[PDB]
Image: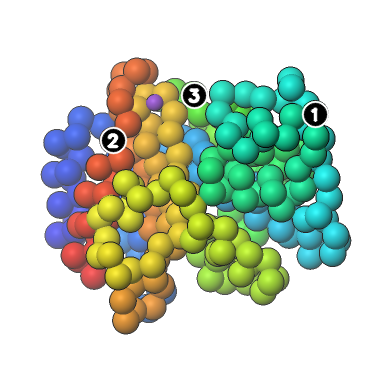
Amino acid sequence: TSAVQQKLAALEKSSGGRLGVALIDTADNTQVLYRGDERFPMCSTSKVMAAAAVLKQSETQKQLLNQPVEIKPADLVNYNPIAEKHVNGTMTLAELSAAALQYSDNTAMNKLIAQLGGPGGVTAFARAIGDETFRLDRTAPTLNTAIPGDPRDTTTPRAMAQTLRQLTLGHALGETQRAQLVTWLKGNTTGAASIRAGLPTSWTVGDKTGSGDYGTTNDIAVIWPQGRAPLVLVTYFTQPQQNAESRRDVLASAARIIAEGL
Ligand SMILES: [K+]
């Protein structure tokens, strides 16, 4: 147990929930884990895998990201700020990817999942790029039920960190596609209260958040620190009671502890 792990344990104790953290520092490829091999519900952080899978498809179909997808009134779910503008019209797969990632539009995520042949298609992509832990089982919104003990729509912090690194900094995608994914993440709108809130302002972040029942509050980020090689940081958090409140501050606090321990 390291100093950083002891600080994260103290944070967890004061929070009353269960915290999972994985850092990869690409300066030396070293890792810092806290409950790194426990399963957590991904919620909307799973949207990175779906978007990446469609990017991979687009490597052998030049026009794919321009392909129109019909949005019907029945397609709208619980949170769909972009898709609801396009009901009885269309969005392109690029537009759906940006909406899913940057606004966490759930209807957009469901169109990505459909483009991949269902939740199993997203899992198949994960396996193809060497992630044996990720599983997507359901569409939105029910992929966010986040029930304790439920293996559906979960991964581990270690696994997600390794996959996010491969996607954004490694060679799981083609160069253009990797750049596009990083551009999308850097343009996230939802992130400022989470991992980013715990880091120095000068550090550049691209991230995807998630939320669900059981006060589940997630964020996965690729970080470019001032004067340092990039990091990849996963922070997962979930609480015992179904109607617990979000705790984005706990993610910020975890990020701060990680930053101060570099
Ligand atoms: K909630």
Q: Quadrant of residue 146?
A: top left
Ligand 1, seen in the image, is in the quarter at: top left
Q: Nearer the viewer, mark 2 or mark 1?
A: 1
Q: Which residue is mark 3?
A: 145
| Amino acid type at mark 2 | Arg
Relative to 25, residue 88 above or below: above
The residue that mark 1 highlights is 88
- Residue 133 is at least partly visible in this image: no
The first of marks 1 and 3 along the sequence is 1
Circle 3: is it few (<14), some (14-19), or many (20+) Cα within 10 Å? some
Disc 1 crowd rating (10 Å Cα; few below 14, some 14-19, many 20+) is: few
* Of pointers 2 and 1, the one earlier in the residue sequence: 1
Which residue corresponds to mark 2?
247
Q: Viewer-proximal residue, 69 or 111?
A: 69
Q: Residue at x 31, y 22 (%)?
A: 244
Q: Earlier in the sequence, mark 3 or mark 2?
A: 3
Quadrant (top left/top right/bottom left/bottom right) for the N terminus: bottom left
Which residue appears at 20% of the width and 66% of the height? 261
Q: How far across and how far down the image is residue 230, in percent?
A: 41, 72
